[PDB]
Length: 161
Length: 161
Length: 161
Image (cartoon, rainbow over all chains, first blue to last red):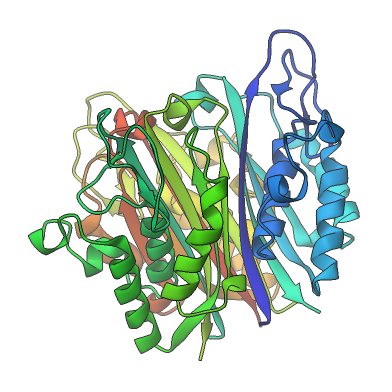
């Protein structure tokens, strides 16, 4: 039972032309709209969490932190990540590595990726070499391209201890 | 050559407002429309199969079970899964673990996941701990959100014997 | 640090009704439009590259080959792949296996997959058994289904040397 694979996927619709400014990978990114979600609305962490729990066959964030429950209204996605990893460790697994892809027309994710990596390496208690983050656009096609929300895909490897 | 990775992806358009009621992960889920496909139309099994065959570098379900061939009109996706695994075993591989994500606005996948896991653990001849299933919506965005079909992504790890 | 996982994702919008004819997985496929990209516009290689670099926590193709830089206007995606792998080897990793899924309504990818596999096995310097390629459509749904562009997802396993 040496190694386990996991996959995550999250999308959030953009809000009004208010503020937010969208938080992603625990980083506050200036933008003229934020994302609409029951929680912090951080698609990168949501997708990373789902990957982790999925690898551990623990379901997903829903299965750990009921979406219905008012205790998680606006809750910090970094907190959820951190709890999820505590459970994974409990079960005798440890992060191998993590690869994330943000899918967004705008804003540019590039400048914020180093800090995102810092946050995750901190949260999954590991060296920053086990964390990789990418962005791409869909060349203006589909709802991400039409500019309506952003999406995120994650892929994870867990190692036995 | 210790371990091999695989990825799958399937989508089916919804039919009329007839019946179906859609079958997914081998589970019959009540819903006012079913999916339109040449076979059973089970996106979770289709995507899981593709992942498995992909990891084994065996192509995909097309390469094993010609879509053109009338012998697979309405064929049980569980049967196809089962044959595909027989071939994978033949080649000296065995499931490590499987993680699936269903992408759908409605109906709720939650209540049916335990049974889906039972079906796969049965079919891939393994303990149910090596099988993980998740759902998410795309927050009403895109064709899954517009309610037009459902999509499924799968990720697999094969181990050498 | 035995094995590392990676994920890639690319999409390109179709051009006019001119020529192109679209190049994918290094194969020239007859079609009445080609893809619109700053480079060769080969979504299969782009996604494969991103997976590789992602597994190596090296960022993505952007981080190696600035999109802004005029030296990569129309550049061969096979060249980029090849350079990326040189860097991965430099860091003590080697391909385990690769699985790719092309997502397209038309044209049919089927007949070209053997040759695509030849190109990659050549480029990643390995036996063709470590390379798997698939296509699917989205049953005419979404922008791939509406026929507006094609998309590609890749998944990779790197082994330590």
